[PDB]
Image: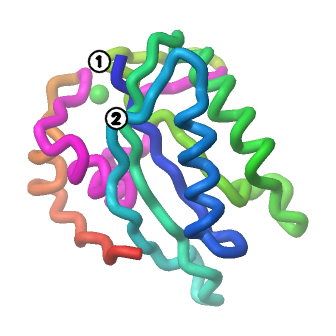
Amino acid sequence: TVAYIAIGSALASPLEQVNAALKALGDIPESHILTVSSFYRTPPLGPQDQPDYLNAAVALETSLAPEELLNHTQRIELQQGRVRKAERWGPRTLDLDIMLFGNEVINTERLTVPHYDMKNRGFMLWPLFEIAPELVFPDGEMLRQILHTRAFDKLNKW
Ligand SMILES: [Cl-]
């Protein structure tokens, strides 16, 4: 099963945090990386201008069940990243999201696939389109049509 995973990171030096994360993803049992998108650069949310965020997408072939894959992405987030001390509820310093899991639709208490907001997020869709331009979502919508209709601005490269 081909899973597509969004990776984000702005902490310390994003390039080596993300590279360590990719190595971790590749070491997930019963799984191997098919391809990784380019690394992209997105500005921080808020006017205060935090560090720049590094965004990418990974195609991972896996025979794990979706919740088993979740277990590993959560483990990697714990091992490779941390919580913001002034915002424990805020996003961690390394973000992994399972965007898509084959053609599966999953609405459990722990796991929602497709990612619930990805169709509204250029920073998830553009890297995905780079590695999977002909992708079709479980509901039949084409990735290309979403990017075209919604007219999301392209992302700058890291
Ligand atoms: Cl869908």
Task: Please give the name of the residue rendered at 34% of the width and 35% of the height, measured from the top-left corner.
Answer: 34
- As helix, strand or loop, the secondary structure at mark 1 comes to loop
Position of the N terminus, as image quadrant, is top left
Q: Is residue 123 magenta?
A: yes
The span shown in magenta is 110-138
Q: What is the crowding at mark 2: few (fewer than 14 residues within 10 Å), some, or many (at least 20)?
A: some
Q: Quadrant of ligand 1?
A: top left
Position of the C terminus, as image quadrant, is bottom left
Please name the amino acid that badge 2 sits on. Leu
Relative to 18, residue 107 above or below = above
Please name the amino acid that badge 1 sits on. Asn
Question: x%, y% of residue 52?
Answer: 55, 78
In the displayed structure image, the side of residue 19 where residue 11 appears, left or right:
right
Relative to 100, residue 119 above or below = below
Q: Nearer the viewer, residue 158 or 99?
A: 158
- As helix, strand or loop, the secondary structure at mark 2 comes to strand
Question: x%, y% of residue 135?
Answer: 18, 35
In the displayed structure image, the side of residue 157 where residue 48 appears, left or right:
right
Which tag is nearer the camera, tag 1 or tag 2?
2
First of labels 1, 2 by sequence position: 2
Residue that protrudes farthest toward the bottom in the picture: 48
Relative to 68, residue 15 above or below = below
> Which residue bears the numbered disc 2?
34
In the displayed structure image, the side of residue 50 where residue 22 appears, left or right:
left
> Which residue bears the numbered disc 1?
103
